[PDB]
Length: 217
Length: 217
Ligand SMILES: [Cl-]
Image (cartoon, rainbow over all chains, first blue to last red; front, side, top):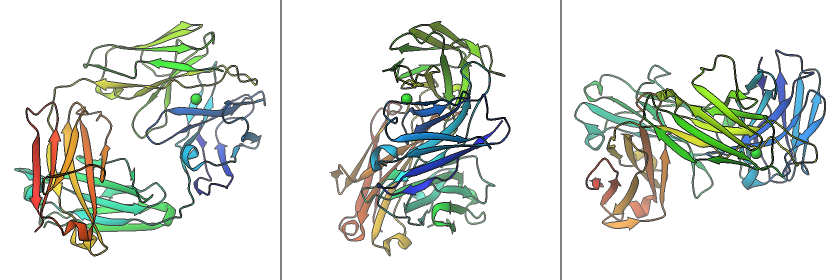
């Protein structure tokens, strides 16, 4: 009762995309597998599904450039060519779904990005707290994670010991074609100077880890 | 070609209230209609299949109805946790592409709470960032409701229209508030041309716009 995608990442506009959905927990026969995708901030979009039947079904926009195959040793695949920088950049989901039975789960999703641009690791800058970031008892600090590509990047605080008060915002794509991200946390202002606040940034695509100390200014 | 029209685009109700979402199909899809819930940062989860049958563990306060062309999802006993996006999709598909597993556009369920004005914090760019040739000024609007809110940057009382990036979180499942990050990006040179940097904020919970500013230095 689990599904996982794989083989995502940065793809060139002429490239051919290939994902694999590994089903480990249920016999593939007599279980339909769907591919859905979601562009950042937008709705769900069905690509196609491969029935338990063995038959294959496609949305009209993907039928001409997509093939779904299964290798019934716990494998199903989506090939998509004519990769369009614009449209095809998105999170790709594979789901076991039964139109008629109470069996349905989706995978976590895998990021796919189409761009002639290349991978870049992030730069982490402090958002030091100051009087312009205090409000009596509370003070705001954070991280600016600037100029990285592609998504995504994960952000922790004090190695996960701080979660209440933390807002990590959706990454935004800059006029330069790179991504930028902000992570902020409200902390007690009296605690500054004695309590240390460390921003843990992980950007697996470029395999970098950073830990910026956010100090008062 | 199958099209799924989901109305309304957005609906809000207090805790303990009721919400209704309607869904239309081009032609009859019999009862092959599923309803999904998608909370921030999560795979969608299927609440309802075959139009009215509830998935395992789903509370009977989710009710699906309809057949042929017009369907409805009604959610009673609203909780803060039901702040999510809700999708219908057809579970009937063909090979000829008359039918397809098409998703509705989506409805955002907003949990109505009392109006709250943002707390405003501002962060000058970091010394370590200026060494690379860029200046980023961040304005942070924290824990407000409802989500409508405009930010305006003024350098020496000159409106900056085109070099801002806004970013906003989804509704919080605990306090039902929003947060918003705005970033003003300048070259180091253009940043050192002026002294007064200010973000003006307009929000329904404040009777007049408020400006938080700073002098470079
Ligand atoms: Cl769709």
